Image 1 (cartoon, each protein chain N blue to C red):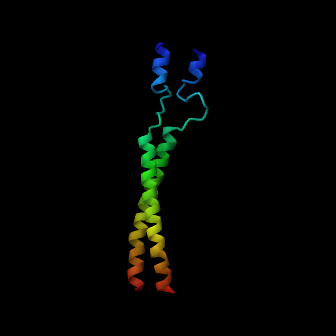
Image 2: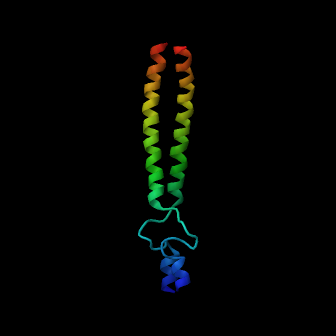
Image 3: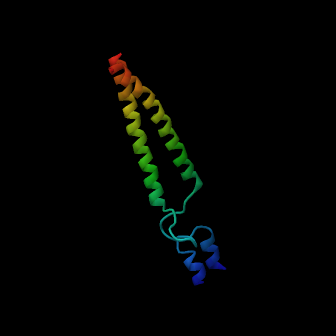
Length: 52
Length: 52
């Protein structure tokens, strides 16, 4: 049971599971990146048009 | 048998189990970032050239 429990205590048999928190941190970081990149691109297209 | 049944379908860590759908969203958002990364860098050199 302890052999199963050590491989079944949330984390699998290998140590250091991908945590959903870090994966959600991964998801939220990208969307924050994508928003700032998109706002930059709108601001970049402003900068492209104006110097033209 | 009950212990293996509970721990074989998602180990109880109160932290979440990683799904491939979330990792695909990791792929999709970041490629969308990289797509917008490439688009801005093209418009960046345009901003470089117009100011120059």
